[PDB]
Amino acid sequence: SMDANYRWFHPAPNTLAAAVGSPRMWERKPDGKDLNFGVVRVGGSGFGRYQSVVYNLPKMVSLLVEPWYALVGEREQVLGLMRAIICQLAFSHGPDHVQMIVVSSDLDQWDWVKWLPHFGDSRMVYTSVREFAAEQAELFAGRGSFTPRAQTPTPHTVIIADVDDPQWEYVISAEGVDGVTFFDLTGSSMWTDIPERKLQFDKTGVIEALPRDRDTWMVIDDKAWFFALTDQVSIAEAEEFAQKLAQWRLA
C-alpha cells in the first residue's frame, strides 16, 4: 500500500531533519525491486479552495525518465522547490547512489550544501559552466546519450543548472547525458523548449506539467494540466536538514 505508507517514502521535506538517522534514511536501492529509486517528491495533490476536501497525496518526478526538468517561475519559488528536491534526495538516497552538483552564479544561496556528502568530490559547487566542465571532464568522457528507464547504474548525478551560459550546449545536447538529470532554474529557451520537461509555476506555488502515468512515468497528454502544489524549503530549513545530516555523519 504505497498511498497508505506514503509518509515513509515521500513525507513533507520539513520533516526530514527530525528523521535523520532513522532506518528510512539512504534506504533507496538501485536493485530493480525498489520502485522509488530515483523518484523525488515535488509537492502535493491538494490546491486552492480544494485543499480542505482533497486527500493530499504526494506528487513526484522520476530522475530516470527525463534527461532534465526545467523549473519555470519566480526566483524564490524555483529555489524553494529545488531545495526541497535536494533535501528529499539527500535523505532517501545515499551518496553512493546519488551525487549532486550545482553550477550557479549565485553561490550565497548554495552555501548550505557544503554539509551534504552528495556534493563531495571524490565540493561540486561551481560558478561557471567552464569551471564545471573542467572539474567534471571524467564524468562526461565516454558517456552516451540519456536512455530513459533491472539494476540501475550508480551513482546517478543530479545537476542544478543555475547560470544562463551559452556554453551549456557544448556540455548537454538534445540527446541528454546517460546517468545524469539536470534541473534548470534559469528558464532559458534551451531547457524550456521540451514540453514534457517543463514544470511551470503560477504565483500561488502551483506547478502545471504534462501529466504522466503513475506506474510508468510515461506522458499521457500533450497539454499541461495541474501537477502539484509545490513543496518549498527555505534556506534556514535546508541548512537545518544539512547540518543535522552532517552531525549524524560525524557521530
Image (spheres, rainbow, N blue to C red):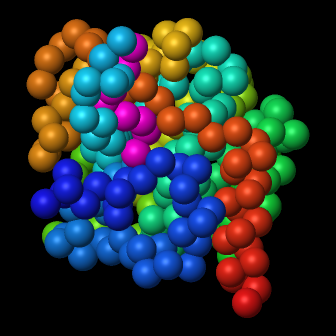
Q: Residue at x 48, y 73 (%)?
A: 25
Q: Residue at x 62, y 24 (%)?
A: 77
> Is residue 192 or residue 52 the one in the foreground?
52
Q: Magenta segment: does it hold 37?
A: no
* Residue 219, x across and y down, in percent: 17, 28
| Quadrant of res 23 | bottom left
- Vertical relation: 228 (above or below) 144: above
* Residue 245, x across and y down, in percent: 67, 71
| Quadrant of res 241 | bottom right
* Residue 224, x across and y down, in percent: 28, 12
Q: Residue at x 51, y 41 (%)?
A: 182
> Is residue 123 or residue 111 the one in the foreground?
111
Look at the image and tell me whether residue 144 can be seen.
Answer: no
Of all residues, the one furthest to the bottom in this rendering is 251
Q: Residue at x 39, y 14 (%)?
A: 48
> Is residue 141 or residue 124 the one in the foreground?
124
Q: Does residue 98 appear left or right of residue 61 in this picture?
A: right
Start and end of the magenta stretch? 41-48
Query: If the image is split into quadrants, where does the N terminus sit?
Result: bottom left
Query: If the image is split into quadrants, where does the C terminus sit?
Result: bottom right
